[PDB]
Length: 112
Ligand SMILES: CO[C@H]1CC[C@H](n2c([C@@H]3CCCC(=O)N3c3ccc(F)c(F)c3)nc3cc(-c4c(C)noc4C)ccc32)CC1
Image 1 (cartoon, rainbow, N blue to C red):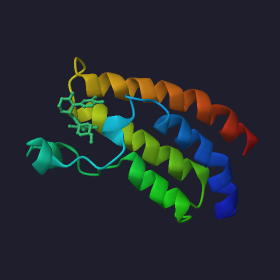
Image 2 (image 1 turned 90 degrees about the horizontal axis):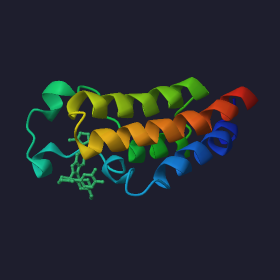
Image 3 (image 1 turned 60 degrees about the vertical axis):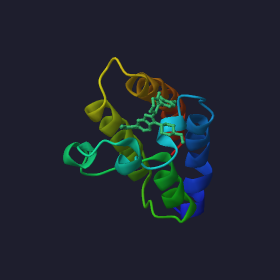
């Protein structure tokens, strides 16, 4: 896969996530535990991930294969479901994005 081919193919799946508003808002920048006053965040989440990081990796051609992109998107979701309680808005927004991602990534992976 050329990185331009991955970027062209996968960027619309990422755009679909950013289009979810307000559901994407907590995911658009890395969690900042100082600002949010949650010093245990990095005790629980050892490999942080967010949309800005994924976007940067796509933009710069850091993914060799599409599964690596998919793995990072799932890492972001898994981190949020891990840290946050299921009653929280952030966990529910995570679930909403995951549903959108599933629906958009499926045909794309098949094309590829
Ligand atoms: C610049 O705007 C942002 C919106 C999300 C704000 N925020 C908020 C704020 C705190 C105030 C209460 C509140 O409702 N927030 C909030 C704000 C907007 C949302 F869309 C949302 F779901 C939640 N909580 C966040 C939680 C997380 C989070 C993620 C993702 N994974 O683990 C943790 C913890 C990330 C961001 C959170 C921080 C400022």
